[PDB]
Image: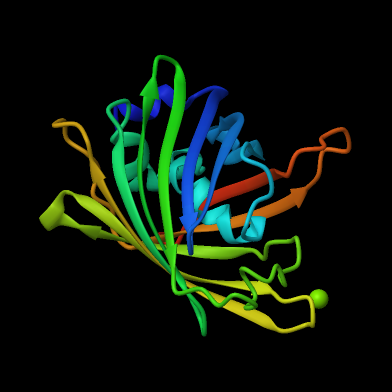
Amino acid sequence: ASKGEELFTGVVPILVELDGDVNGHKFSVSGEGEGDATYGKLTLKFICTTGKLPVPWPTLVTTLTFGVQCFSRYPDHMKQHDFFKSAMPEGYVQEATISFKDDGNYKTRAEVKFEGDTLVNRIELKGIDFKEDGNILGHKLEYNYNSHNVYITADKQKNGIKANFKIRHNIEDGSVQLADHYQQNTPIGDGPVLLPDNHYLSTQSALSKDPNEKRDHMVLLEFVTAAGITLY
Ligand SMILES: [Mg+2]
């Protein structure tokens, strides 16, 4: 267990700021909400502040929530495996490559750290090689998000962690759009961090709309629980 974990015993306010460019379609997203790691619970509202989002909202969920993996519920018996909180408050840098099968890719860079008592995530996203009337730029994905695992492994070399997982977005015709994810996280601070044994994050997400919101937006309720390492 770590000193960073003490920062997460109660409800913590969250800010997310994203600048994106996908095939030259530029956009920004701002998110606000809060996290309660005791319950692995996230409540966030994201708004496209530049007009219409040029990609489907579900394709941004992992990018927008990458940095809030510090709100995962680690069972007590697994708390020595929680890198994310151990890096706080100084934070970490995160990079990911998200490869959409038979389409383009996102590359992201982000920094997550505390700013006072708020957990702040700042993200840059670059997407290239998308098909103009593919499932992403053609907006052919359902507004939903399947439950999934995020497989974590240590990168001791680099004093950090990696994650690998596949997302299966639902296409409106009943098919699936696969998105391969590779994530790397590195501490910003010089203090010690927890380098975990292999384990995963079990994630469940519900996407909705604010009925009074006329801007392009996404309301997200997400639960994230660590598992995979195991008295009666
Ligand atoms: Mg369907």
Figure quadrant of the N terminus = top left
Residue at the image position 66 percent from the left and 81 percent from the top: 176
Q: Nearer the viewer, residue 37 or 28?
A: 28
Q: Tell me where residue 35 appears, x and y as whole percent.
A: 57, 32
Q: Nearer the viewer, residue 149 or 107?
A: 107
Residue at the image position 37 percent from the left and 42 percent from the top: 79
Residue 125 sits above or below residue 82 on the image? below
In this rendering, would 156 be left or right of 214? left
User: Splitting the image into four quadrants, where does ligand 1 fall?
Assistant: bottom right
Query: Can residue 207 be seen here?
Result: yes
Q: Tell me where residue 63 appears, x and y as whole percent.
A: 49, 52
Picture colour scheme: rainbow
In this rendering, would 178 be left or right of 97? right
Q: Tell me where residue 222 appears, x and y as whole percent.
A: 64, 47
**Farthest right residue in view:** 211
Query: Can residue 1 be seen here?
Result: no
**Farthest left residue in view:** 157
